[PDB]
C-alpha cells in the first residue's frame, strides 16, 4: 500500500525486481534536487528513488530540495541508506547498524523550511529522529536475513568533505556516538518538518580515524561499499514487500 | 540610567509602564526585528525590543538590535529568554539566572568585527553576563519568593528545531543546565559594544529525554502564559 | 627543499635571512592575505606568508594555493594560543600532535561547488610527523620550555571563549586553543602539503587565569615570545 | 505513622518537642552510634538517632538502621551537611537529592554479606522515597525557603575532604553536592524496605569552587545560619 | 583442555560426561564448590560453579583450575545492558573492562611473597578465545556483539540511575558484579581467559519499570540454552 | 628546613650524602616499611625512607610518615615512578604534579580512624605544597631538564597495571600520569601538617598508549635511565 522513497547511492536501484520507468527533472521552491526523481514499482508498491549526489560534496547537497520533491511526488516513508565510519568497537567494517538517535555536528547547510519568508515559526520536536515502525521493519528484515547488525546506535553527523581527526573521534566517542557520516543531517529533520516518517540504514565502510592501525583509504571504502551494497539490497527487498 | 529589555511583547504589559511612540531605525548592520518602544517606568527611561519582531531565532538581526539600542541610549540590557530544562532541579515553571553559557550556534552574523576594518578586536568573554545585573535579578527573585536558580549554564543552540535526546545528553555532559536558541550571539554582541547584559531564563519545557513524552508547542505556550507574569514582577523590581 | 612559513611579520626579522621578493599572487579562490615574500636562508629557498594582512574571515584557501603554486614543499605555521592544560602557561611553546575543529562558516575545502569528483581526504593525523620532529628536535637543542605533543582546539572568534566553553574544550581533551589552526591544516593536506604547527601560549585560557584576559597582557607575551620562536625557525630552516 | 530522623542532635531542639528518652539497643550487626531517643511530635511518634557520639567511614549504619526498623520506624528522614559542587547550590542552600553516586568503599554496606542461604540483589534505581521527597519539597515551598527540588549526591569516603581535581571528576560524573554520610545508609534503608529521603544543607563550596581552602570555621558558621532553617522544615514534615 | 566458569546448568549441556567430582583445598581458602572434570568431543573439561559476588573466593577458584590443568577459561556472566544495542537476551563478547569493585581478594601478590609482580593487563580478555566465541556465535546465527566494555561493580545491590549514567559516561556497555578480579587473577596465573556475557536486564533507568528478579530469571531461563549451544561448539 | 626523601634506594647514591644505618622504630601504627636512615648532605639534615623495603597497597604509609615526623622531618619530597597518560609525557619525562585523583581503597588512609574522641576532616584542595613544587621546578629549570610544571596524578590500586578502557576513563577524568604509591601518602602527610610534594618520573606509556604491551624490563631500563636525573634534582633542592 504505502509509497516508499529510498535515498542513497545508485546501485540501490539494481535491486532485483525493481522497475524504474520515469524521470521528471523537478524544479522546487528551494531549488534543484540532486538528480531527477525515479518512480517505479516493487513487489506491488509504488517506489521512489532519489540519488543523494547526482551525475556535489555532502555539505552542499540540496537536501531541502530533495525532501520537498519526494513529499510532493507522494512519499509517505523514507528509508535513507548511509555510509559511515564505525566508532564503537563492535561496529566494524561491513556491519549494519540501524541508529535510534543522532548528534548533529553540521553547519551552514540549508537545514529548515522555517526560514526566509514565513508567517509563524515552528519548532518541531525532534526527540527521536527516526520513525520507530520503520526502524523495526529494518530490524525485522536484518534478523530474518541473519545479517550482523546493531538494532540501535547514535549517529554522529559531521560536515566533511574531509574525514575526522583522531582526537575528533575521541570527542564523538565521549559524546556517545557509535557511527559517523556526513549525510544524515539535515535530512532527518527536514523529513520531520514535513511529517515524513524517516529511518536510516547504515553501512560501516571503515573504522573511524584512530581505530584501525593504518590510515583510511578511499579504496578500503570503495571495496567495502561494493561488498555490502548487496546486503543492503536484500534488506530493502524485505522492507519493501 | 537607561535600560533595554529584550524579550517578547507581554513584557510591555508591565503595570505602571507608559510607552511614547516607536521610531523605525536604520542601522549600518541592516534592519532591527521591530521598532524600539521608548518608555518611562518608576521614573526611569526604558526601551523595549521584541526580538523575534515571526523571525526564526537563527535569522534575527541581533547586530542590528544591539546597535539600535546602543544608539538610542541603552546602558544595561536584560534579556528574557525561553528555555529547556536540562538540570533535574529546573522543571517547567523554573526561573534561572545563568552565570555562564556555551554557544552551539553557527550561521549568524555574530560580531561587529567583520570585513576589512583596519583593526580587529578580540573581546574577553570569560564571564558572559554582567554580575551587578545578575545580582539585581537574583535579589528580585528572592524578594518575591519565586522558584529560581542563582546560577546555571546556558546552552545556545541553532534551531529552529528542538534537540535530540542524544544531543541533550551531549549538552548535559558539557555542563549546561538549560538550552535555548536566542542567547548567542546576542550576549557577546552586547560586550563588543561595552553594554552590560544579563539574561533571565524561563524554563518552558523539559529538554528532550527528561519528560515522558515528546515536547508539544501546546505545553510550551502554556508555560509562557503562566510564566510571563512572574517575569514581569522581576523586571519591575529591577527597574 | 623549500619551506614556507605562515605567521606574523617579524618572523622575517630573522637574522641571516636575505629576504628579497614581495610577490602579490592571484588565486582561483581570490587574494591571499599579504604578498608572498620569497627569500633564501641557509641556502634553502624560503617562503613567507603573513596570514594577518579576523581569523574567521582569512582567505585560508588563497594562502595555501599560493604557497603551493610558489613551490612550497613543506609548511611551518606559527600560532598564538590560549593554554588550557595547567602545564602550558604564558610563554610555553607547544608542538601539537592533534586538533579539534570547532569552527564554521570558513571556506574550508577545495572540493566545493561545481566539480566532477569529490575527495574525502584522510585526516587522522593533522600534522606531519617529520616536521613535528624537526620542531621538537630544535626546541630540545635550544633548551626551551615546551611540549612534544598536545591537542589544538580551533575556535571561531574573534571573541575569546567563555569559562564554561573552556571547560567543555578541556573535557574534550584540548591542551590549547586558537582561532587559526583550521581549516589551514586541512587545506594543506588537500594540497598534499606537509604541515606542522608551532604554538606559543600568550594567555591562560578563560577561567584559568585570575581575572579577564586583556589584549595588553597578550601583546607582552608576543613581544617576549617572538624571540624564542625565531631561534626555533632558524634551527628548523638550517 | 512513625518517622525517624537521622542527623546531628540539636535537630532534637524543635520547639514543642518532648524528648521522652530512650534506651540502649543491641543488634546482630553491632552497637548503634547513640542510644535511640524516642519522642512525640504533635500526635506523631518520632525516633531520633545521631550518627556520631566516629568518622563517617566507620559509623555503623547497619546497626543504626536495623535498630530503627526494630523500634518500628516506617519512614526515615536523613539530614546531611554537604559541599556544594553546582554553581547554584552555594553555602546555606538546601537541597533534596533525587539521585546519588557512591564513591565509598571500606564499609559494612549490606545485610546480605556473610555465609547466608539466599542472596538478594535489591534494585536501587531510585535511591530516595519519592513520597518522602515531595513531603520535604512541599515543606520547603510553604516556608518560602530557597532550595533545590532535585540533585545528585556524591558520597565520598572521608575523613579528608576532596581534591580540586577530584571535584572536577565528581562534576563530570554529574554530581551536584558532596557528602560522606549518604551511603551505604540509603541502600541499607532499602534492603529493609524502609522509605528514606535526605535533606541536605550545603555548608561549604566544594574544593576549588572558591579561591581559598575549606575551613572548619566556614562550616561552623554555615551550620549556625543553617540549623534553624533545617528544624523548621522538620516541624512541618512531622505535623 | 578448557574450564568453564558459570552457573550449574551449564553442565546440562548435551554431549558432556562429568566424571570426577573432587573437592580441592588451596593456599587461599576454599573454592566456591567442588571441581568437576569431564570430556566433551574428546577434550578434557573443567567446570567450576562460582557459587555473594564481593565475597566469592575468586582466588581459590582460579588457582584450583590452574592446578587441575586448565589451559584456557571461559567465564559466563549475567549482566545488565547499558548500550542501547544490547537489550535483554543479547549475547556480548566483551574486549575491555573497567573495574569499580574493591574490598575483594584481587591478587596472588599480597601478604608474605618474596617477589611482587605488576602484571600487564592492557587486554583483559584473550583474543583467540574471543575469536572462538565470536566464530561460534556467527555459525549458530545468534544475535551478538563482537566487542564491548564490561563494567564490574561491587554489588550485591544494583546500581543507581546516576551510577549507570557515569558508567555510560565511562565507555561501558554492560554491567556485572563478577567479572573482576576473576579476569585479573586468571592473568596472574598465565591462564588465557575470555568472557561471554548474557544481558538479562536493561541497566537502571534504561527501561520502563524497575529491575526485578522475576524479570532477570526469565531472561536467564530464556538465554541459558543459547549459551549452552555456544559452549558446545567452542569445545568441539 | 629538614627534608625527608621518600623513594627507592638509588636515591641514596647522592655524592657527599652520608647515612646512619636504620635503627628500627616502633610506631602506634605498626612498623615502617624499611630502615629509616638519618643523613647529612654537606651538613644539612635529611631523612631517607625507602617505602617498599610488600606491594604498593599494603605498604604501611601511616607508619612511615609517623616515623618520619617523630624523627624531625619538616618537609617531604616523594619520588614516584608512574606511567604517562598524556601524549607529551613519554618515557623518561619528569612531572611535578599539582593535583591528584585517588582511585585506591582498602588502605589505611587516615590517622583519624579508630574509636577516638575527636574527628578531623582536613582540607585537601591542594594536595601538593606550592613552595616545594617551585623548588623542584626551579631546580629542573636550572639543570635544563625536560619536565612538566603541573599535571594530575591518578593513584590506582595495583599491583596489576590498568586496562586500556581504565586508562581511557582515567584520561577522561583529566589525569596526566598514573602510579600506585601516591595515596594515601600525600593525605597522611597533611593530617600531620607536613608540606609534601611529589616528583614523578615516567617509566612507561600507560596501558594502550603505544604499539606493544607493557614489559617489566622496559620499565626497569627506564628507571636506570632517569634515576640519575632525579639524583641531580635532589642534590640541588638539598643545597
Ligand atoms: O569515517 C568517516 N567519517 C565521516 N564520514 C564518513 N563516511 C564514511 N566514512 C566516514
Ligand atoms: O527544549 C528546548 N531546546 C532549545 N530551545 C528551547 N526553547 C525552549 N525550549 C527549548
Ligand atoms: O584564549 C584564546 N582563545 C582563542 N584564541 C586565542 N589566541 C590567544 N589566546 C586565545
Ligand atoms: O566538602 C565536602 N566534602 C565531603 N564531605 C563534606 N561534608 C560537608 N562538606 C563536605
Ligand atoms: O543491572 C545489573 N547491574 C549489575 N549487575 C548485574 N547482573 C545482572 N544485571 C545487573
Ligand atoms: O602504568 C602504570 N600504572 C600504574 N602504576 C604504575 N607504576 C609505573 N607505571 C605504572
Image (tube, coloured by chain):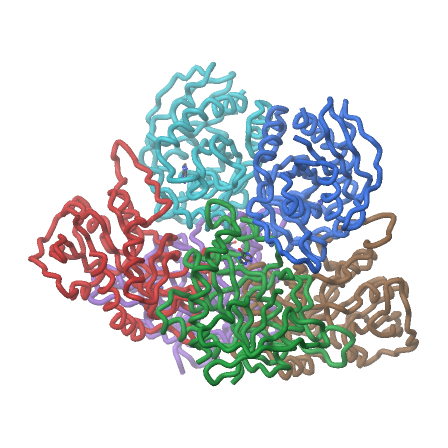
Chain colours: A purple, B red, C cyan, D green, E brown, F blue
Residue A209, position in %: x, y? 55, 50
Residue D195, position in %: x, y? 55, 78
Residue at left 15%, top 57%?
Answer: B34
State which quarter of the image contains the N terminus of chain F. Answer: top right
Q: Is residue D160 left or right of residue C174?
A: right
Q: Is residue C205 above or below residue E71?
A: above
Tag count = 0
Residue C193, position in %: x, y? 49, 35
Residue E215, position in %: x, y? 62, 82
State which quarter of the image contains the C terminus of chain F. Answer: top right
Q: Is residue E94 left or right of residue C111?
A: right
Is B95 or A13 nearer to us in this picture? B95
Inspect this view and state whether residue E39 appears. Answer: no
Inspect this view and state whether residue C60 appears. Answer: yes
Residue at left 60%, top 83%?
Answer: D72
Q: Is residue F87 above or below residue A4?
A: above
Amino acid at each position: 500500500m504505502s509509497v516508499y522513497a529510498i535515498i542513497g547511492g545508485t546501485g540501490l536501484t539494481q535491486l532485483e525486481g525493481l522497475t524504474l520507468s520515469e524521470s521528471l527533472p523537478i524544479e522546487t521552491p528551494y531549488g534543484a534536487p540532486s538528480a531527477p526523481l525515479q518512480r517505479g514499482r516493487y513487489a506491488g508498491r509504488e517506489v521512489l528513488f532519489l540519488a543523494r549526489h547526482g551525475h556535489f560534496p555532502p555539505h552542499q547537497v540540496n537536501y531541502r530540495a530533495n525532501l520537498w520533491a519526494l513529499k510532493q511526488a507522494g512519499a509517505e516513508a523514507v528509508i535513507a541508506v548511509n555510509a559511515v565510519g564505525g566508532i564503537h568497537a563492535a561496529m566494524g567494517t561491513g556491519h549494519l547498524c540501524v541508529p535510534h538517535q543522532l548528534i548533529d555536528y553540521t553547519s551552514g547547510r540549508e537545514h529548515t523550511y522555517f526560514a526566509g519568508d514565513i508567517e509563524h515559526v515552528t519548532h518541531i520536536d525532534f526527540s527521536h529522529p527516526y520513525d520507530e515502525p520503520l526502524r523495526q521493519r529494518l530490524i525485522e528484515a536484518l534478523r530474518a536475513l541473519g545479517l550482523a547488525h546493531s538494532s540501535h546506535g547514535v549517529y554522529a553527523c559531521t560536515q566533511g568533505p574531509r574525514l575526522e581527526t583522531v582526537a575528533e573521534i575521541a570527542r564523538l566517542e565521549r559524546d556517545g556516538n557509535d557511527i559517523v557520516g556526513m549525510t544524515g543531517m539535515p535530512e532527518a529533520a527536514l523529513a520531520r518538518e514535513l511529517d515524513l516518517p524517516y529511518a536510516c540504514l547504515a553501512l560501516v565502510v571503515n573504522p573511524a580515524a584512530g581505530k584501525s592501525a593504518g590510515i583510511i583509504t578511499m579504496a578500503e571504502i570503495e571495496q567495502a561499499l561494493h561488498d555490502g551494497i548487496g546486503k543492503v539490497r536484500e534488506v530493502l527487498a524485505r522492507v519493501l514487500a
